[PDB]
Image 1: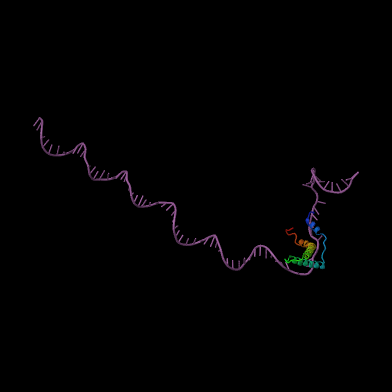
Image 2: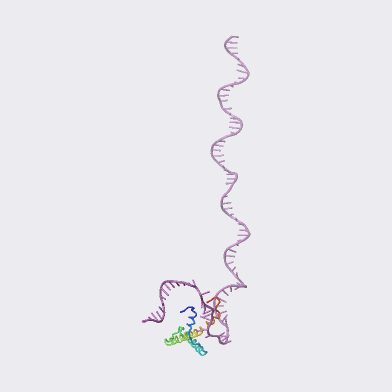
Amino acid sequence: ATADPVKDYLKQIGKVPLLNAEQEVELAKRIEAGLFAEDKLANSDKLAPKLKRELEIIAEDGRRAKNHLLEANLRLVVSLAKRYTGRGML
DNA sequence: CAAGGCACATGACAACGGTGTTCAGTGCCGCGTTGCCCGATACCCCCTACCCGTAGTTGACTGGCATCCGGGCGCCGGGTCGCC
């Protein structure tokens, strides 16, 4: 909590793990795994409770991987925003 | 010389003259205002042209910006860390 909140935002980015090819391809594999898990859960057909909880856990892990990609690439957006700054928008 | 007999005019007499009222009736005609007939018009339709919003675009491309000093001047007031 300081002045010039952009500096605070960069500090909020902090140190996060940059992803090498294997890392993000595996992460996206887990993303589509969670996608299929939630697709199965959304179906009105009855699924066993333990299987439904497992699918929910897989979907949650997928969400975490999404967040990891977001935070890792936060640095990428800040550079792109600088690429367009100084045109009447903050 | 006085009395009796004839002319012209005379006290009224109505009835025309001419015109003024009045009745009483019926209109005459003053303006106000109705019933027409047209021209334009606002209000439905169809058509397409162009504005306005939405959705994509695959080598790679991973942290920015320039601040700010010569007020000046003092005070309040709180915070802030030493102090013994």
